Each structure stands twice: as C-alpha cells, then as structure tokens.
Image (cartoon, rainbow, N blue to C red):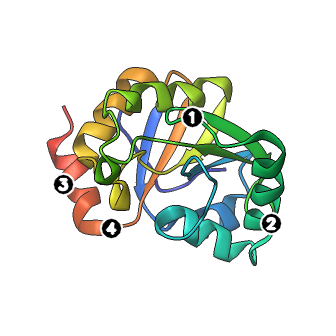
Amino acid sequence: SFSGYLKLTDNVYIKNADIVEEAKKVKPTVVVNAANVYLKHGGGVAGALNKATNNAMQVESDDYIATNGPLKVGGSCVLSGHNLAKHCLHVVGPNVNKGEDIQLLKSAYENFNQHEVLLAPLLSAGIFGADPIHSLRVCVDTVRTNVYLAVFDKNLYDKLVSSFL
C-alpha cells in the first residue's frame, strides 16, 4: 500500500514523488492522469505516464477519442492503467495557459469522488498553469475519497506542506 505520505486531512495524503515511479511501485487501483480534452499525452504528468506505458496509453486514448469525441474541461474518463495501475482516471483540469475557467478545477476534482482510493497529481498544476497551492486547497475541500498526492518537485512539495492551512 501507500508509504511515506504526510497526512494533510482525514482523506488527503501527500508525498514528494514521481507519480510514474509511485504507480510502478504501488500498482494502485486508480492512477489519475492530468489529461487534456483530446487525451493527447504530450508533456507533464500525461507525457510521463504515457511514456511509462510505452505509448499504449496514447493508442488506447486515440481509440477512445475516435469513438467518443473529446472530454469536457472538468470531466474525466476511466481507461486502462496499463503497467501503472488497474485503471487510469484521465481528468481534465482547466489549463490556465489556454484561458480556461479556474472555477472548473472543483468540477475536475469531483471526478475523484467516484473512486474510493486514488494516486493523483495536483490538477491544473505544472504545465497547466494554475497555482498548485490553490489546487491543493480545492483538492482538500472537494475530494472526500482517499487521495494520495504525488508532487514531483521537492521545492514545491515543501512549499505546499509548509503553507497548508
């Protein structure tokens, strides 16, 4: 099970970890991907998770998009976790660098409530352009299920823990 996490609340845990390495070690039921509406896993967490699957995530995702069309910002879909997890919950947080409504971050985190336990990154953080401190706040105030947050950057992890109210 999950090890080395700092407990933030009754249901939110955090660790300075590479989510790919964490997923490969734990093989959780659900790993969350920081997806975009097209499931084009080019960079950030999505690029890293997809590369770890040897592009199998992208091949599955392209078939999903060909059948269903794009996701909504704030939406999600469940696909295979490949070699990383039983399932991957692809969640689309708003991309601030594309002018998307930051208010959709709460809707994005609501997708986590459909799963009892998840390994996840901070939505809309990193290359999605939102303030990770704000993302953690929305996470703790929205997610009620057990979420294990992996924060890649040590310096950001320390800032998140030390500023956590």
Within-10-Å neighbours for mark 4: few <14, some 14–19, many 20+: few
- The residue depicted at 17 percent of the width and 48 percent of the height is 162
Q: Mark 3 — residue?
A: 159
Q: CA distance from mark 2 to mark 4?
A: 28 Å
Q: Mark 4 — residue?
A: 153
Within-10-Å neighbours for mark 3: few <14, some 14–19, many 20+: few
Q: CA distance from mark 3 to mark 4?
A: 10 Å
Q: CA distance from mark 4 to mark 1?
A: 28 Å
108 vs 154: above or below:
above
Q: CA distance from mark 1 to mark 3?
A: 31 Å
Amino acid type assigned to the residue bearing label 3 in the image: Lys
Badge 2 element? helix
- The residue depicted at 75 percent of the width and 55 percent of the height is 85
- The residue depicted at 48 percent of the width and 31 percent of the height is 109
Badge 4 element? loop
Amino acid type assigned to the residue bearing label 1 in the image: Lys
7 vs 114: above or below:
below
113 vs 41: above or below:
above
Amino acid type assigned to the residue bearing label 2 in the image: Val
- The residue depicted at 68 percent of the width and 58 percent of the height is 26
